Each structure stands twice: as structure tokens, then as C-alpha cells.
Image (cartoon, rainbow, N blue to C red; front, side, top):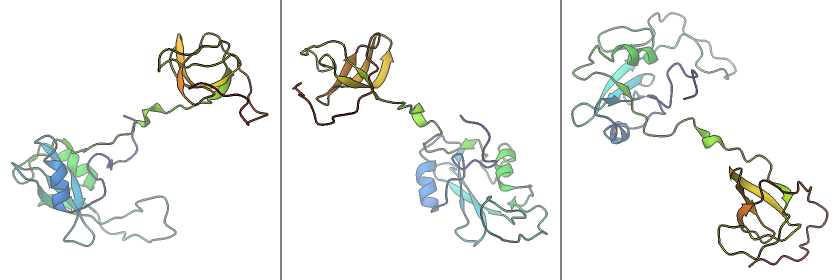
Length: 204
């Protein structure tokens, strides 16, 4: 998780509209009590709630007004300024659409109740991609090589820690281009730059 960003949360229930078949296609793929929302394929300016009921997934047309701007951008677009309830679905009334999914969770739409957002996949993770620096170390030992995983480098070779599994061996690219283990407990932080014409190069 990341926190509070979208009062309606797009990656949760409202992705970016499509055809009931599409929503359905994914909906059924999730938990039986899963339901997502789509765009009013019938109405020009309205929302639609989709719900995997029984074997398929039915839709519920929502009616939105829009009293205030939706997104920060947009040069100028004067809003209505009258629609009180603004958003509503079925034969009842609610403040907004996002809020609707939070109340009907136990009110029962037309036969089925709302439980959680479909969420087919994707999530704010980013797999914490560091990639901090890279080329800034000069090996201090020569070795022909025995294992494909071990980085065979020659004394004075400026490698780049391609990763750092543990403090007892890291990953780095050698003058040849291959990677492997490197001296994490003792390496030469040697600023490489002056030739770039390959002096010798002889690994495999």
C-alpha cells in the first residue's frame, strides 16, 4: 500500500471504462463477491457499476452531476452549481459515486452485495528499483574463473556492482562484459575515465 491518493481509487474499482464483456471478463476472474465499475455505455455522461452476480456480472447505471472540477489541470470549465446529491444509483441517494461502493457493501443492490474491488492486477510497488551508481570499483585480485556465476576479473579491473545480495559477495560486470561475485569487503573505489579504448580485455 501507499496511502490515501484517490478518494475513489482508480486501481481499485474504477480503472478506465470498457465494454461490460471486458469488465465481466476480468470480474469473473476474481472472488465471487467481486465488483468493479465502468462507464455509462448507454448514457453520455454517467457511471456504471458492474457486479459479478451468480455466474456473470450485471451492471448498475449511476447518475453523476459534477459540481466541482475533477482534476487540477483544465484551463477553465464552469461547473453546474445546482446538482445537490450529484451522484446517485438505483432508487436511493448518495453523496458521490466513490462513496456508493462503501455503503452498498451490505445494503444489497438488486440481489448481490458489494464486497471488494476487482483489482485484476498491478499495484504501487515499484519493486524498489535502486540502481544507485554502478561503475566505481577496481578489483584487487586476478582469477581465471571456474564458475559461470563467479566474476573472473584481473587486478586493476574497474567493475560495477550490478547488485549487492550480501556483505560477503556482490554482483559486478567485468572488463569482458560478464558479471558475477566481487570483493565487497575490499575493492578499489577508482574513478574510471581516461581511455575507453580497451587496454587488453581477455576473459572468455
